[PDB]
Amino acid sequence: TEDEKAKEFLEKFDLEAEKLYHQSSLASWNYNTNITEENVKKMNEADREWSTFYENMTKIAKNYNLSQITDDKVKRQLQALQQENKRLNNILNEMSTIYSTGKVCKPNNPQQCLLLATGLEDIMQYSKDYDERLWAWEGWRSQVGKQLRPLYEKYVDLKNEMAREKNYEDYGDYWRGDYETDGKEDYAYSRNQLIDDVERTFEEIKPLYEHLHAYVRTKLMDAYPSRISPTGCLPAHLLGDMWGRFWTNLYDLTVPYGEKPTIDVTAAMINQSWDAEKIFKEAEKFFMSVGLFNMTQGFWNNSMLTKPDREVVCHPTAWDLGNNDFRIKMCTKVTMDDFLTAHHEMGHIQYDMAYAKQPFLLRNGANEGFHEAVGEIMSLSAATPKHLKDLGLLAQNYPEDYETEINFLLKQALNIVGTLPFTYMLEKWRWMVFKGQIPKDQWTKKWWEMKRDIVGVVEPVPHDETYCDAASLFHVANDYSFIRYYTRTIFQFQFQEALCRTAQHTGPLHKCDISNSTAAGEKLLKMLELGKSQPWTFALENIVGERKINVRPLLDYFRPLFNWLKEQNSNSFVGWRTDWSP
Amino acid sequence: TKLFIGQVPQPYEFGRLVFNFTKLLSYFQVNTFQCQKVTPESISLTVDWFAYRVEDKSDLLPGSSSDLQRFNYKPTYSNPTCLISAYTNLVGVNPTNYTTLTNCYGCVDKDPANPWGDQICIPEFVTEVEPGFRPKPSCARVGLEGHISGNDTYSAIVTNGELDSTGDPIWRKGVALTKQPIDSSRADLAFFVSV
Ligand SMILES: *[C@@H]1O[C@H](CO)[C@@H](O[C@@H]2O[C@H](CO)[C@@H](O[C@@H]3O[C@H](CO)[C@@H](O)[C@H](O)[C@@H]3O)[C@H](O)[C@H]2NC(C)=O)[C@H](O)[C@H]1NC(C)=O
Ligand SMILES: *[C@@H]1O[C@H](CO)[C@@H](O[C@@H]2O[C@H](CO)[C@@H](O)[C@H](O)[C@H]2NC(C)=O)[C@H](O)[C@H]1NC(C)=O
Ligand SMILES: *[C@@H]1O[C@H](CO)[C@@H](O)[C@H](O)[C@H]1NC(C)=O
Ligand SMILES: *[C@@H]1O[C@H](CO)[C@@H](O)[C@H](O)[C@H]1NC(C)=O
Ligand SMILES: *[C@@H]1O[C@H](CO)[C@@H](O)[C@H](O)[C@H]1NC(C)=O
Ligand SMILES: *[C@@H]1O[C@H](CO)[C@@H](O)[C@H](O)[C@H]1NC(C)=O
Ligand SMILES: *[C@@H]1O[C@H](CO)[C@@H](O)[C@H](O)[C@H]1NC(C)=O
Ligand SMILES: *[C@@H]1O[C@H](CO)[C@@H](O)[C@H](O)[C@H]1NC(C)=O
Ligand SMILES: *[C@@H]1O[C@H](CO)[C@@H](O)[C@H](O)[C@H]1NC(C)=O
């Protein structure tokens, strides 16, 4: 009989929820595409009304006995709602502020200080001076990282108390609940299962990373003579980044064939008189050819595809306003990055439209990594030489070249492969901290031991337990989970392989375009339409062919590069020793 | 009759010429006659022809997955087309053996400072024949060498007059396999006839 009550409750919830959601989202849109004092006020009051509504109906949902609900979709909708605070909010607000306003002052003039986004990021990206790079690196951690120590310690204790009140072992266990699902046979997924799968896939990547690491090492040894040992770890500050999250900026130092330029169609689009409207129209027909949705009349009216000439946020985003109202906000230029971004952002819209028929509470991605992975795969297809050629942007008789393929694959690897050990190590450290596996007074010690053993990166400067390197990163200081980036990358390749298989593509995986492939489109759509109505393992199977997490497709994608690296390292040490430091 | 005069080309260097079927059937003994998008009774016209054994005839058939149609010769057959597989004594001259390309893939230079030096070859960079076209000349040359080396499966890294986007030589690693005939006193030929 409670199955019936739950249903009428959810029906009433949806009727009010959609009305309040739409007006709240509209107010936010209006602010972002205008920015006025009047608009921020309207946004704030609109958000307030939705928030009070949602919380009031959460309390009601929690009065239902979930164990006696028969209809699984009703069960999941109830769960969407059902699933020391003052002190914690004070800690969280202070941590965010310290990060945001952090600056590094010059040693010979304390009155002149650089902020992260005003100069320090440019030093880490462009500087080739060992000592200038070290100043920015150590300065950031000394000035900001040492302020977040006592706050991160209080943060961890308070978060664990919260998680345990909700019957979790700790806050790390709480976070891993985002992958937990019910289901028959092996569709169910446990919270501790994520750990086994993450470690399992990591061990299969190592060989690729060790060769990539060795290659980069020999290039940096020339850039920085007598600074780097041929058998040791790489200095943290020489990776082209404040944290070493990506190796993207090392491309200019590592490029295999510097005389072999990559494809760039910026000039082609300029000569052919392209604009933002043209770019999005071309993206639209791409999605139609694979067999997905076309854009609605509202999309083409109320979107902001160009920067107005107001004060606006030009950051590319895909919006779902509610009531079949979809928009994109993006200050589009005619380059090549914005061309490919248009496909990324429209890919989000395709997903949002696909599950528009689901119950309000189930209108989301099956998993936190699914929504972004879909965007990425559509973007990759549109970047292939044959797509650019068929668009009339790349010369029809453009000469083939194998060296440029190696240059391309390495650039991709520096961003995609060189980041995976970072995500793995960072999240693993936090999990151990929350569990209590790492003692309060061994946080720094383990951070650097793990980083040297797992990533192969060594601290330029001796640090004691007054530093907090983890909290020197945005996501840690601002209380965000990080594992989503690890799983997203793996799913991205599982999706692309399955679609290129469906499309009957024979050749290197990096040269696959799913255009004119309705079969690939139909297979993709089947997964997109599910939203959160099913376990992500079920949704995964519908597009991949298997319900398990599989890193192999990633390793196959970069296989041509792996073979190249192996021969390049014939006379080099592969791997690293941790007994060396600068 | 011109196509029966002189020697018979290998699959990777198939002959092509452009211009009475019953008379042709009086030159050779046909084993298999099949047509795609055309009635055999009905068959400008063009013929693509090369030496190929009868025993491995399966490889000549449309829709088949084989090395022949991947690295040597693939018929697009956009025009209506017929396949004739037959054997005959040309004494032209009969083939001593049959050579087929089994693989070909691209190579990059180990040392960027020397485009003519040692190469690193990547198996994944597969170079396959485009329908109607001959194999690339850095692929076909390996087949030509394999047909004479004596090794029943010859492999080599070659370049043959084709340049990249900068003007440097394109190197490719090819693999050719040579098959010995069962009947040493006859030629086995494949003919692809299109309107
Ligand atoms: C397939 O048939 C061809 C002939 O149509 C065979 O080619 C012949 O192979 C022999 C043995 O290697 C060659 O003789 C050698 O010539 C070199 C000089 O290049 C000499 O140094 C050696 O001492 C020996 O005399 C012969 O010249 C060559 N025929 C031609 C026209 O070049 C081929 O070996 C056969 N393949 C297989 C697997 O049986
Ligand atoms: C940006 O916001 C301002 C408000 O700060 C909008 O200006 C109002 O426009 C309405 C008409 O729609 C007038 O009735 C109000 O009197 C105007 N108020 C002010 C203070 O000027 C402006 O139109 C908005 N711009 C866009 C593109 O929406
Ligand atoms: C919460 O919802 C119930 C529905 O019965 C309503 O009576 C109550 O007034 C609501 N409370 C608030 C603060 O909106
Ligand atoms: C109601 O909830 C309790 C847990 O508080 C559970 O033990 C009980 O079995 C539930 N009732 C039914 C009919 O499932
Ligand atoms: C395109 O390039 C050609 C030169 O090849 C030039 O003559 C022409 O004016 C250019 N058109 C535009 C729109 O830039
Ligand atoms: C695009 O969608 C609209 C929906 O109103 C439809 O009328 C139009 O025919 C569609 N065009 C194509 C090519 O599907
Ligand atoms: C879009 O704008 C045009 C202005 O030409 C208007 O006629 C049309 O009704 C609008 N459509 C929508 C969905 O707003
Ligand atoms: C898809 O096919 C159309 C012709 O029907 C062609 O114009 C377009 O470029 C193709 N897209 C690809 C292969 O990317
Ligand atoms: C010839 O055959 C031998 C034995 O298999 C092999 O070692 C050699 O590399 C081959 N040479 C060529 C050119 O294939």
Image: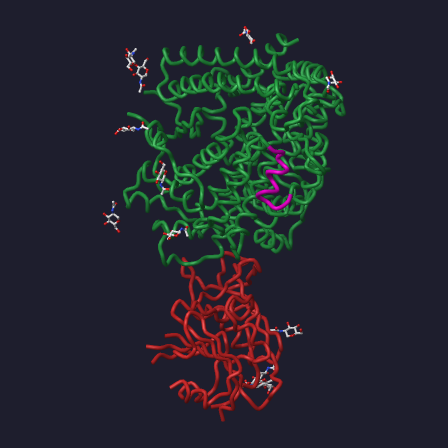
Chain colours: A green, B red
Q: Tell me if B183 is positioned left or right of A305 in this view.
A: right
| Count of numbered labels shown in the rendering | 0
* Residue most extreme to the bottom: B91
Image: A89 above or below A526: above
Position of A158 compared to A393: left or right? right
Q: Position of residue A493 (x, y in %)?
A: 57, 44
Quadrant of residue A97 within the rendered picture = top right
Q: Position of residue A225 (x, y in %)?
A: 58, 42
Give the camera-side residue of A151 and A35: A35
Q: Nearer the viewer, residue A253 or A495?
A: A495
Q: Compared with residue A475, is residue A536 higher up or lower down, i.e. above or below? A: below
Indicate whether residue A540 is drawn in magenta. Answer: yes
Q: Residue at x 50, y 64 (%)?
A: B128
Vertical arrangement, residue B187 with respect to residue B72, above or below: below
**Quarter containing the C terminus of chain A:** top right
Asked whether residue B175 is drawn in magenta, I would say no
- Report the magenta stretch's main SS: helix
Q: Which residues are magenta?
A: A534-546
Q: Position of residue B42 (x, y in %)?
A: 39, 78
Quadrant of ligand 1: it is bottom right
